Image: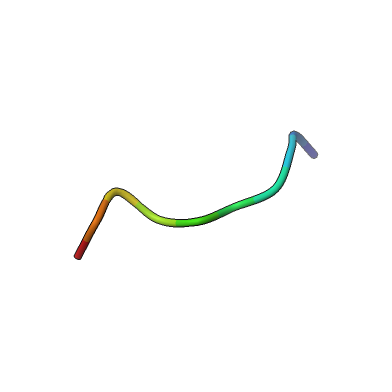
Length: 10
C-alpha cells in the first residue's frame, strides 16, 4: 500500500 505505481523506467 503506497501511491501510484509507474515503474522505475523499464
